[PDB]
Length: 114
Ligand SMILES: O=c1nc(Cc2ccccc2)[nH]c2[nH]c3cccc(O)c3c12
Ligand SMILES: [Zn+2]
Image 1: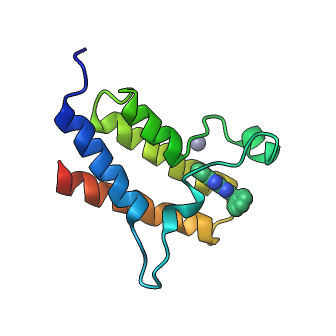
Image 2: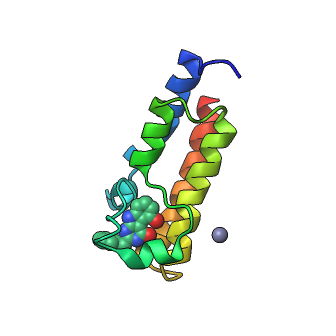
Image 3: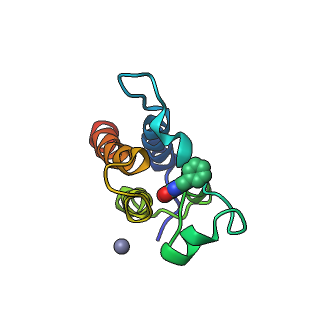
C-alpha cells in the first residue's frame, strides 16, 4: 500500500482518545482496566482462554507503528478487545458491560471523526 497519511494517524488517535477518555454518569473512566492487560505470569488463565489478546496500549502502538491500514482494521482490533472482555468475564459483570459501552463509544467516535 502507501504510508499512513498524517490525517488518518490523527483520526485513529482522535478516535482512540475519545474511547479512553470517555466517562459515565457516575464519573468513571471505563477504559481504565482495558489500557493494560495483566502479564502472562500474573494471569495465565486469561491467555489460556483468549487466543488473540489486545489492550489499548497495544492498539496505540499499532497506530504509532502504522499497522492499521484503514479505520476498518482499527475497528476490528477494538471489537476484538471488547469480545475478549466479554468472553473472559461473566455476563452482567462490570468489565463485561463496560466493553459493550466502549464498543458503542468507538462507533460514535468513528462516525463523528470520519
Ligand atoms: O478481561 C479482562 N479482565 C481483567 C481482570 C482483572 C481486573 C483487575 C485486576 C486484574 C485483573 N483485566 C483485564 N485487562 C484487560 C485489558 C484489555 C482487554 C481485556 O479484556 C482486559 C481484562
Ligand atoms: Zn471469539
